[PDB]
Amino acid sequence: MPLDPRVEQFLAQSLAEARQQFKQGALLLDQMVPPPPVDTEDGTVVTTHGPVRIRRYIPDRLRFSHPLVFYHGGGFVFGDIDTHHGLVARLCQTVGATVISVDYSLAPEAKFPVPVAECIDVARWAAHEAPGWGLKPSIVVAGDSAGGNLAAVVSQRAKDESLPIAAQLLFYPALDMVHETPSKRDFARGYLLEADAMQWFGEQYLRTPDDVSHPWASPALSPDLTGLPPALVITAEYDPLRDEGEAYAEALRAAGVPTEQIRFDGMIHGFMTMPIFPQMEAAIEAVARFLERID
Ligand SMILES: COC(=O)c1ccccc1C(=O)O
Ligand SMILES: COC(=O)c1ccccc1C(=O)O
Ligand SMILES: COC(=O)c1ccccc1C(=O)O
Image (tube, rainbow, N blue to C red; front, side, top):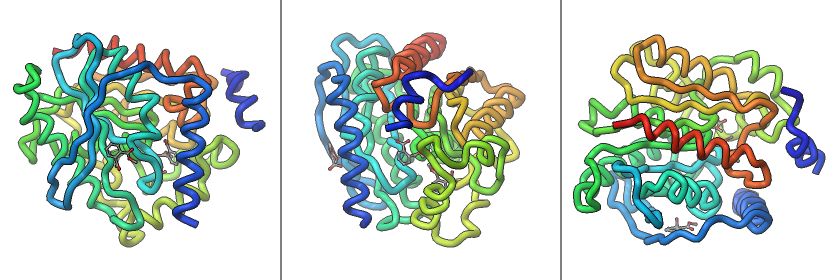
C-alpha cells in the first residue's frame, strides 16, 4: 500500500529518437531479467488497412485451448513485438498458450481508428486459424494500457463483427479519454505515465479532439456491457488510469459479465513489462489461474 520498495528505487532512477529510446529501455530491463526461451514464428496478416506484422509464440507444452491475441501498449505511438517480448514469452510459457503478438500501425502515421480495425482483423484471422492449430475457434484478447484499450474495444465489437472471443485480459488499460478520475488527478505526475504524455498521445492518435467521446476510443462509455467476454482487469494502485480500469471492471460485473478485478498495491503503471518487479510474474500467474476458469 506504501509504494513498493523496488518501484521507489526505480522511479528515483524527435519521434524516431523517442521510439528508439523507449525500445532501448525495454531491452535494458530484459537484459537485467532475461525472458524464458520460447519458440516463435513471424508472419504477416492481411488486414483492411494493410499488412500487419505478427509473432506467434508456441509454448513448450500446450495447456490452454484458445489462442491469445496480444496487443502491445505504448500510447498508440510507441512499442513493438520486441518491447513486449518479456511479457508475451512468459504469458506463453506460464499459461501454456499460443500467443499472437501484434504490431498494429502506430500513430501519428496512422490515426484512430485504424489500429482498432487492424486488431479486429487479426483476431478474426486467429479464430479462423485456431482449428488448424488444434485449438478452439474462440480467442482470448489481451493488452497493456493502449493495448488494453484495443483489447476492450475488440471485445465490445466482437458480436457485431461475428468474432468469437472467449475472454478479455486488460492490463492497466486506458478506457476513458473523456473523464478526469481521482487517480488521473492524484497520480498525474511522477509515476512514469504522466498527464502531459497522455495529452500528447491523444494529439498523435486522435483525428480531432471530439474523437475522445467515440466508443471505439473510449469503451468505458458504452451504455450496455451485457454479454461481453469474461474479463480480467488488472490495475496498479499508483496509476492515473487506475480508477477508469476499476470502474470498468465494476460495470462489467454489474452487467453480469464474469469479471476478476485485481489491484496490485504499491505498484505503478507498466509493471507487467518491468521484470525487475516480482509483481509482473505474480500478475502473469493471475492470468493463468483466471484462464483455468474459462471454458
Ligand atoms: C519491431 O518489430 C518486430 O520486432 C517484429 C517482429 C516480428 C514480426 C514483425 C516485426 C515488425 O517489424 O513489426
Ligand atoms: C501509457 O500506457 C501505454 O500504453 C504506454 C505509453 C508509453 C510507454 C509505454 C506504455 C506501456 O504501457 O508499455
Ligand atoms: C496510454 O494511452 C493513453 O494514455 C492515451 C493515448 C491516446 C489517447 C488517449 C489516452 C488516454 O487514456 O487519455
